[PDB]
Amino acid sequence: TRRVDDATVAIRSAINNLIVELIRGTGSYNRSSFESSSGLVWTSGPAGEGSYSITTPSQFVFLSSAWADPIELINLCTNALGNQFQTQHARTVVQRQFSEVWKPSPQVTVRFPDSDFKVYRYNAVLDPLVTALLGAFDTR
Amino acid sequence: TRRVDDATVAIRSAINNLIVELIRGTGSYNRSSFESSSGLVWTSGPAGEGSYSITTPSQFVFLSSAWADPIELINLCTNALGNQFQTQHARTVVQRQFSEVWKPSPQVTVRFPDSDFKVYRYNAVLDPLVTALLGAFDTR
Amino acid sequence: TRRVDDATVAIRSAINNLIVELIRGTGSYNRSSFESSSGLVWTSGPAGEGSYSITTPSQFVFLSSAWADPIELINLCTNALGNQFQTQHARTVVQRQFSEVWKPSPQVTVRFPDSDFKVYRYNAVLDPLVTALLGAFDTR
Amino acid sequence: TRRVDDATVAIRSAINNLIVELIRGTGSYNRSSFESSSGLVWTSGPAGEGSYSITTPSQFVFLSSAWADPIELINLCTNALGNQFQTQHARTVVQRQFSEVWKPSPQVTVRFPDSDFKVYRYNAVLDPLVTALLGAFDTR
Amino acid sequence: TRRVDDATVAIRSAINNLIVELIRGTGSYNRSSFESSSGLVWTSGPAGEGSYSITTPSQFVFLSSAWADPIELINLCTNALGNQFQTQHARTVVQRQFSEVWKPSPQVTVRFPDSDFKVYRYNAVLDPLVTALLGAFDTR
Amino acid sequence: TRRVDDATVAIRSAINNLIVELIRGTGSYNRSSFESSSGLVWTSGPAGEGSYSITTPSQFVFLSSAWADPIELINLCTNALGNQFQTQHARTVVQRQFSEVWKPSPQVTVRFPDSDFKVYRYNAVLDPLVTALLGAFDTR
Amino acid sequence: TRRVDDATVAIRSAINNLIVELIRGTGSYNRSSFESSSGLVWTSGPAGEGSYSITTPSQFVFLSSAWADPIELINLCTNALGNQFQTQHARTVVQRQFSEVWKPSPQVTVRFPDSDFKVYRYNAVLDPLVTALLGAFDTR
Amino acid sequence: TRRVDDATVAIRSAINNLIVELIRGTGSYNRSSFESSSGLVWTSGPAGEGSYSITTPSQFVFLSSAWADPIELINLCTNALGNQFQTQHARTVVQRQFSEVWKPSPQVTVRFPDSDFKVYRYNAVLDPLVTALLGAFDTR
Amino acid sequence: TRRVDDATVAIRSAINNLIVELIRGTGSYNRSSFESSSGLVWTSGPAGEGSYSITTPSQFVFLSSAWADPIELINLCTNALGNQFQTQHARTVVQRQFSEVWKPSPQVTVRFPDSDFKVYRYNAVLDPLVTALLGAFDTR
Amino acid sequence: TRRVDDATVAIRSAINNLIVELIRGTGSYNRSSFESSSGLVWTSGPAGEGSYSITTPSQFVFLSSAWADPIELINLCTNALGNQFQTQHARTVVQRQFSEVWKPSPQVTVRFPDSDFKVYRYNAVLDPLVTALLGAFDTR
């Protein structure tokens, strides 16, 4: 009963399904698109600090630990496709890597970065793919 | 008989079902919505202290240990989805994390925080999801 | 023959059935409602002491060790839902916690607390639920 | 052959059937009701002593070791419902507790207490319930 | 059950399917074709530095670690075809070699090399072949 | 190492040391001597009850479980001298018998018996002898 | 190495040393002596309730769980002297009995009993004796 | 090598050394003494809330989790002295009890309780005693 | 050879040596003291963002992950003093807790918090104590 | 022969000796100091590219993979001080982390970053410390 031979196919197909949308750029925001689609308005208070105005609680997801650099994420994918997923060590390490890539960037008193782009963990398209990928590593 | 292969699917689907409602913001209150929906009225007694006026015993649930920070809770979810639920250690640790995230914030002599938001453990929509999630970790 | 996998479902469903009524506040009394529904009349004898007037023996249940703080009880429930009921240690500890939460508050020479609320162990609606819950922990 | 799983149900159902009647107060007497229903008449002989006048031998049951305080008995019940009756140690300890709660209070030269209430072990309604309860603990 | 005799055939056929397209040069770009097909425009800012103008997030794939020298890649293929894929050591080593050949060459502040050619990891035709090849080495 | 051959000698010598003083009657009181030496005064209140007047707390020993019938005690001694103290069963049984012979006879609302005699457990001469005797049975 | 033969002597001598002072009544208080020596003043507020006036924190020991009935305590001693302290079961049971005899009687809103006496756990003479006794049961 | 026989003596002597100072009341503060000795000034801002004014960082210890009810703490001591410290389970449980008794009561937005008293974990006299006591339970 | 009995003493003494200085407040900064002692000057650029002016590279330590809340740190200490350092699990968990308490608060584009205080990991007095403490958990 | 107890001390002392110099900022360069001390001159050729002019071969060390971000390196140190160096897994993981932090930043066709700082692996003062640190992890 080689259940590891079926988990490897699922892991690889999940990585590929995530790469398909990462190539298109879907789920990537800058300051403009973030503040436009999230509804958060930055009030540039005096003098060097400021804050976002929270109007609804559903916006608290945007200020959590749910952002990653696009280049770093696609590099994680390209290096993960070249691992021996027959072993448990690799399925643990790359799962930890895909779970720790999501770090906070926007906060209540920290505006979205000026020129950089960030990938949203809970984007409508990336949420199911990243969830399925993280769940594909869960095998005995 | 790999009963652990079925418990992992249930745990992950429960985390996802909870994330679906956490994204929508359902179950999150501020001072205004808390004091409106709970019926508690804050009497600003002299001078720096005060208290809520308890009219019915059903209001005692609101002043218990049933509140969590939305960002902290969704971060628990995002970090939990990247764990090896095939092992018992993880199913115990993340279960303790989802059971201890609920702390008291409103009390009899402590008014609801002024500007922060809190997630209600016994909200009508969040209660079944959190209960099922906590129960999904209970496997031999 | 995993009889422990069926006991966990019963324990969790009993905790939920009790929480459903604890949320509604049913079974919680203050001084007014206690002395009204129990028939006990407080005679304020001189000078700083007093006593309840016992008219029928059925009132001796009210003066036993059958009262708990609502917040403490619902907190026991919320923390109990996050335990590993697959183990015997937890089924013993939380059972002892649900058995020791009932302490005396009204006595023959001790009037019901002035402003606090208490939950009655032998309330018509709470008695079957608490009994079934305490019995759900009894598994080999 | 788990015969212990059926003895636990019987023990719990017997405790509940006893609690049902203890709540109603049936089987509890004071000085007035005891001396009225038992037929014993206290002759206040000189000077500080006295005695009951025994008219029929059937009254010797009333002066035996068959009395308990109602609060103590119902507290034994409320604490007993939270024991692990899967073990022999508990079935022995709580059985000894239900067998030793019955102490003498009226005697030939000791009148029934002035103001206290006592529960009669051989009351018509409590006798079968207490007997069945004591017998439910008798399992291998 | 010699599953290794079937994995070797798949590995070799994948290597051949990749070599067939590498021979035609498909997926190989220079500065002109890269900046034409990717949409990136190099602004030769003062004085010795410069940058590409990012118009859409889908362009972040081009600036990742997804480029390799054509000669080095075809040499990896020609030397890989002469390995003992019956052993796990070889299937691991050559898989790591095919996973590490992809290095970054264009960046935000690093223009595409002037005269050299590079092979694009996520080219429309080479992406499935390289993915299938990397997946063919994953056998127990 | 026959430590049981030395414990038997000590047990028998302790029984004899107790019998020597029991023969002389030392430590035996009636109503007169009890109420004289203890300081307790019986107030023959109306009508058939009464009580002792407690003047100092040191008198609470007299109203405890520290009285035995002289004939019963000397019979315990005479039957105990004919046991096989080489066995543990006998050393346990007769020790329990010498520990349970002390029962309460005078109480707050129970005057000393009119004509009977009683042996005081904490009499100045009998206390050390009874203590040493009870301690002689404690051997491995 | 019979360390149990030395622990038994210490246990018995500790029980005797405690009995010596219990016989004298030292450490026993009534309402008068309690309110005199503790400094607590009872303010008989309207109408049937009241409270003690706490002037110094050292008085909080008096309102803790540190009181026992004298008769019950001396009965525990007299029955404990007749146990087989060679066994661990007895050394555990009687230790639990000497640890649970101390119950609360005076509280902030509960005045000292009118006519009864109570034994103070932290009396200057009884504290070392009770501590040494409880510690004498601690043997492997 | 019975190292447990020496750890028990240290645990008991540490509990006694702590009880000696708990009896004296040292380390117990009310609102007046807390705000006097800590230097914190409560500014009764409008309307029902307020805060302490932090002048030096050394004051942050007072607002941590370092407060306990005096009665609860001395009750922990009196019940702990009656445990079998020869076993590891007890040394773990009572250590957790002495480590969790310290809860926060004063906070930045929560003034010290009006009339209650609290015991300070880091009081100059109680800190070494509590530290040594917690360390006495640490044995293999 | 119980090397674990010596490591516990070192761990506890290190925790105490750190608590001694945490009580004094040494190593805790606010915005004023941080920007004064570090030399960093905040330039309030337009409009809602800003940055510190880096004059020497030695200032990069202040902007790393080396800050903790004083209350959180001292609470880690008070809860750590109540652990079983005889076990490896505790020495690992509390070491991870003392290693993860240090989080970034000042950054290049994130000014020091306005009113909060933070504890500096590399303070001249706290660095050796925290280092020795972290090293005390390192035992086989 | 616990050779692991001496390797841990050496590892920790090496980490501390490196932190001592990282705090002072020694070994950190910007564009100005790098191009000044290394002798490399950037010729701003047309139009958006350029290059350093290599005058002596000793300058090839500066353009290798020998640069790291100061914050990242000191964070590696602060997180490394909290590891269990008794285990081989940690000594391998943190050694790989200290070996992979050094990445290339200046190249022949890539000028030193405009505003960032970098730490030089082969600085005269940091080279021996980093070498000793990397060598301290090499134990059986």
Image (cartoon, coloured by chain):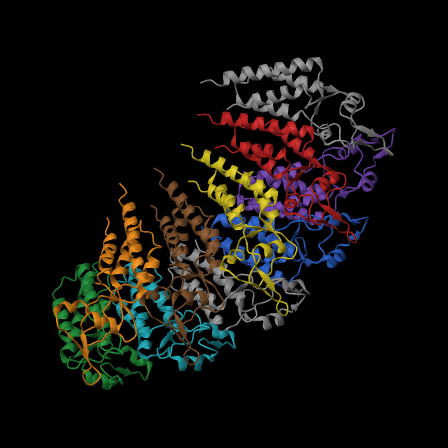
Chain colours: A cyan, C blue, D purple, E green, G red, H yellow, I brown, J orange
Q: Give x and y (percent) for residue G109.
A: 71, 50
- Report the residue at 31% width, 49% height from top: J86
Please indicate whether residue D117 sits to the left or right of residue E24 in the image.
right
State the residue in front, J46 or D112.
J46
The correct choice, above or below, for G45 with respect to D65 in the image is: below
In this view of the protein, can residue E109 be seen by the observer? yes
- Report the residue at 62% width, 66% height from top: H44
The correct choice, above or below, for J103 with respect to G138 in the image is: below
Q: Give x and y (percent) for residue A46.
A: 48, 78
> What is the tally of numbered marks visible in this picture?
0
Please indicate whether residue A37 sits to the left or right of residue C114 in the image.
left
Please indicate whether residue E15 sits to the left or right of residue A3 in the image.
left
Q: Give x and y (percent) for residue A35.
A: 43, 80
- Report the residue at 30% width, 65% height from top: J70
Q: Give x and y (percent) for residue A137.
A: 34, 63
Which quarter of the figure has residue E130?
A: bottom left
The correct choice, above or below, for A6 with respect to J8 in the image is: below
State the residue in front, J1 or E99.
J1
Which quarter of the figure has residue C19?
A: bottom right
In this view of the protein, can residue D2 be seen by the observer? no
State the residue in front, H47 or I25.
I25
